Length: 8
Image (cartoon, rainbow, N blue to C red):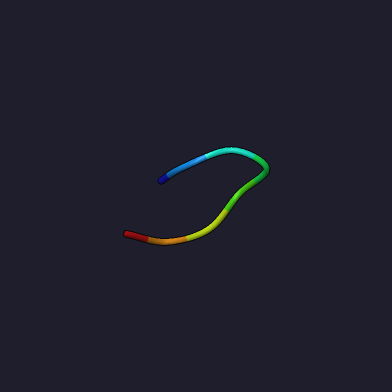
């Protein structure tokens, strides 16, 4: 997961 907290 990529900051600030998005699911990839």
